[PDB]
Length: 167
Ligand SMILES: CC(F)(F)c1cncc(C(=O)N[C@@H](Cc2cncc(Br)c2)C(=O)O)c1
Image (cartoon, rainbow, N blue to C red; front, side):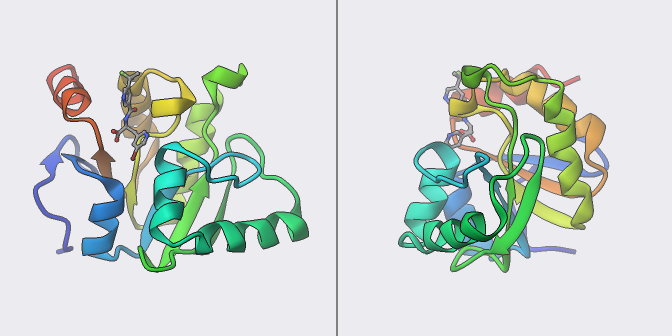
């Protein structure tokens, strides 16, 4: 039993809710919140900018130190950093950005990072400003993630479309 509430169950292990991931993180304090990161951990907009703003820029400060030490992530890769006031940990995961021409096949590799964590609160990778089709992202999520994932979808119209078209 966990503290996630109001989710619709899509599969044995994938759940979905129309919610603001920032507000959901603030209420649940999950062990892991996933950030829709880029390879530079520059949290300017989309989910990343919203999460970072909610940490009063502490996420960005920590991220800049991480990059200065380790260099950029790989597209499809991830790193675990602090969750600050939102979660115990933040798993920064880099999905491919279609608006940069990155290969969409890397979306499966990106979701594989979720399997290293038993339970996660997450957005749909490569959705929103990353330019992928969220319906495709949900399909890859369901077919790749085996751990328990609670997906927060900010846009109500998109949420209803994701549920209604789900196979
Ligand atoms: C063009 C379109 F029709 F596909 C479209 C339009 N608007 C929003 C999205 C979207 O992917 N939203 C997700 C992911 C998300 C993105 N950025 C910020 C947050 Br916070 C959450 C959501 O709401 O959870 C997609």
